[PDB]
Image (cartoon, rainbow, N blue to C red; front, side, top):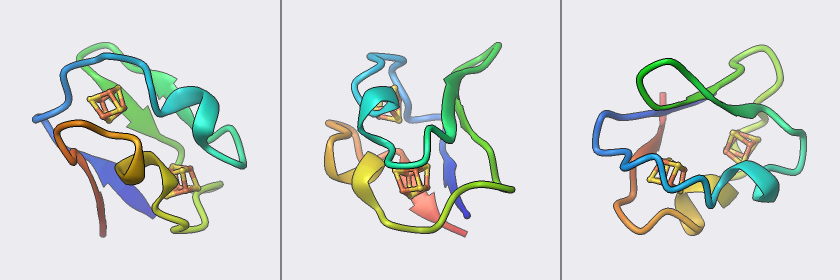
Length: 55
Ligand code: SF4
Ligand code: SF4
């Protein structure tokens, strides 16, 4: 699992790019479903603030 850090600016860009649809807008920011994420890094790759990190 990657996890989206609080640097997230809630731009939405990563949501459509996750190959497994593991991202949603959460209550405070975007959030990753750790039961689906496969660590591809694509979300970080489209993130202007580099908020998703491998955890
Ligand atoms: S690392 Fe890959 S699988 Fe995990 S949330 Fe980001 S885009 Fe989706
Ligand atoms: S691309 Fe980055 S800043 Fe935009 S919603 Fe996703 S994690 Fe947040």
